[PDB]
Amino acid sequence: ASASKRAIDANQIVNRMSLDEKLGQMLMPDFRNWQKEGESSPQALTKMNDEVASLVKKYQFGGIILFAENVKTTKQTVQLTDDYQKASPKIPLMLSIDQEGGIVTRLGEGTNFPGNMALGAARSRINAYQTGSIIGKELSALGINTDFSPVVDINNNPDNPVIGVRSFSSNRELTSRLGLYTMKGLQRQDIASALKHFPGHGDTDVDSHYGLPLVSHGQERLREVELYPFQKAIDAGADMVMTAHVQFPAFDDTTYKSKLDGSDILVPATLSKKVMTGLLRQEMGFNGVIVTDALNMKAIADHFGQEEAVVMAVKAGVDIALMPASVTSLKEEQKFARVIQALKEAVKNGDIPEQQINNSVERIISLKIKRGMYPARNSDSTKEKIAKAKKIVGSKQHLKAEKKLAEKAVTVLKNEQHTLPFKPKKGSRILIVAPYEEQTASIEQTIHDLIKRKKIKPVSLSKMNFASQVFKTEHEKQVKEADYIITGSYVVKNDPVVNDGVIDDTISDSSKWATVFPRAVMKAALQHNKPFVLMSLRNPYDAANFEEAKALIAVYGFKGYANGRYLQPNIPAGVMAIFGQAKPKGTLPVDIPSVTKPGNTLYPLGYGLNIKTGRPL
Ligand SMILES: CC(=O)N[C@H]1/C(=N/OC(=O)Nc2ccccc2)O[C@H](CO)[C@@H](O)[C@@H]1O
Ligand code: NA
């Protein structure tokens, strides 16, 4: 009824459009940085200028994707989005963002949240809904109306360099569940939500930012695992699906000549009709907006021309070509005209039926209608909008929420003989060991705060940043003088040197600092009977690098503290747990493969301890 009227409205609006305006809607560029007339190279775009406004009016793009560069402050963001909607000549823009929460956030002053895998660790599907709801509220106040979230890739390859903690789980049901509820949470605030990255990027060991990944599983495994959370959310009302620049020869074994080396490469799903029309649109029944992942990524740009990529995606069935060309000043603006003209030539010849363009643009208009983008609802002043958004974005209540989720997500994997919590006597020396300066700064700040607040006795603190370092006598001396030692380990792909089950602790350089260094610190604390706790900070699989430790947590998020601000809540939440000020309730959303005993799991999915009793939760 409202759905029936919305489809007729989109049809009428599109029937009244020129081919140029229709192709424009199908493009979503970024203007992350810009080099205005007179400037010497592209700077962060935080305020609108009449140059960028002129390409929006010229080309009538359907929307713009914002990056951190564009959204550093709430004040500046409300003004940019008002200003953008001001430049769009006929139809309100989709203003989109990667506010995933956790390790992928953009909003300068917003609530960052622990991230998907921390949500998986917390289990409860209402927390994913509350995250999607709070993000949705913050984006709304800011005038951003699209979120490229949730990632519903299933992270079942622990060597995954691009997804990892951006996934809820290695388990299809947990991911599906938390994915559906994030989506509902966003759609509830009128934010269009995109599932990504279809048909499932969770098994790759290559980053599609850097080259073209291959998933070689059959259709039966692909339907039961990778597709699963997509189908559930598509049925449930998914607004949009984002594609994956990844090859699936079980789905489409069409090859193309790589612009790079002339070689035969399997097509990336983004550019396959079999996957985007056959599978997604038809078998899977998705009639919402298909959007490319960024076409600037090397998985695409290495092997396909610029115009040629855009044309091949649309031919495959996508509605929106995301980041089709990077134009950073007025002198490169013809890149856009060239994509538009290539599409026109494709319509003219009939390689892309103009009716296909119509159906695609209708979808886009209809989403803009469905989510209240069009007509533009708000009649407040920019000044009023900035006052209001200032009270909502990064609000105290929102922080309370992020604090609670981050603390619950904390997973304790070992705590022998009540090593945790640390209850330090006054004047104890606490050694903080972490890869980077911001991480040691975060742990220090949380501790300082704990002292300030009379939660713990006064201790002195010392830092040790070990990225690219070799463990030297100066370091062991610090461990020796320490009363308590807290060490953060950081891995993406876990690749310690190991020979017949023995992690090689004889390496005397710092190529393998990420595994060899923290293991060195451990071995010195254990040799000297120092209270020692290992906190895994990114991918949890490094838990296998410390079987000797008596205490060991994972927090699923690695960003620390710079410029007076915590860039994630996960490290503070683990530090609270360590000092007794928080109750971790987390259980592993993934298996941790044994390092000493290849082929065995060390900690099963769903394993996690009660920090007080030491019994599995
Ligand atoms: C696999 C993945 O992380 N793709 C992301 C993504 N990947 O592309 C880039 O942002 N551009 C790029 C950065 C470094 C190297 C090559 C391309 O872009 C989309 C929009 O920004 C995100 O929504 C997608 O999640
Ligand atoms: Na991709």
Image (cartoon, rainbow, N blue to C red):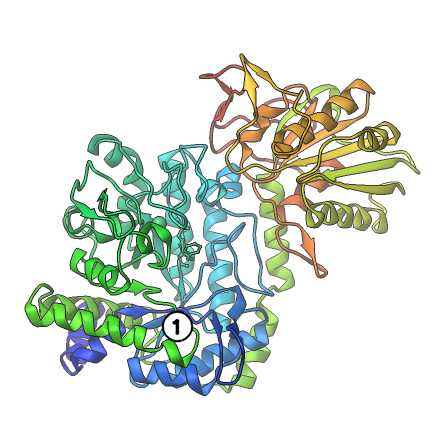
Nearer to the camera, 214 or 541: 214
Residue 118 point in image, percent of width and height: 53, 42
Location of residue 184 (image quadrant): bottom left
Nearer to the camera, 127 or 429: 429
Question: Quadrant of the image for the C terminus?
Answer: top right
Is 511 rendered above or below residue 318?
A: above
Is 179 rendered above or below residue 485?
A: below
- At x 47% / y 48%, what residue is drawn? 128
Nearer to the camera, 48 or 281: 48
- Helix, strand, or loop for circle 1? loop
Q: Tell me the kind of residue under disc 1.
A: Val
From this viewpoint, is residue 378 visible?
A: no
- At x 66% / y 50%, what residue is drawn? 560
Residue 251 point in image, percent of width and height: 18, 40
Question: Quadrant of the image for the N terminus?
Answer: bottom left
Residue 293 point in image, percent of width and height: 34, 56
From this viewpoint, is residue 137 visible?
A: yes
Location of residue 374 (image quadrant): bottom left
- At x 21% / y 53%, what residue is drawn? 286
- At x 89% / y 35%, what residue is drawn? 428
Nearer to the camera, 42 or 100: 42
How many numbered markers are drawn?
A: 1
Location of residue 520 (image quadrant): top right
**Residue matched to label 1:** 327
Q: Residue furthest left?
A: 350
Is 27 rendered above or below residue 148?
A: below
Residue 538 point in image, percent of width and height: 57, 40
Alpha-carbon neighbours of circle 1 within 10 Å: few (<14), some, or many (≥20)?
Answer: many
Left/right of residue 87 with respect to residue 441 in the rendered view: left
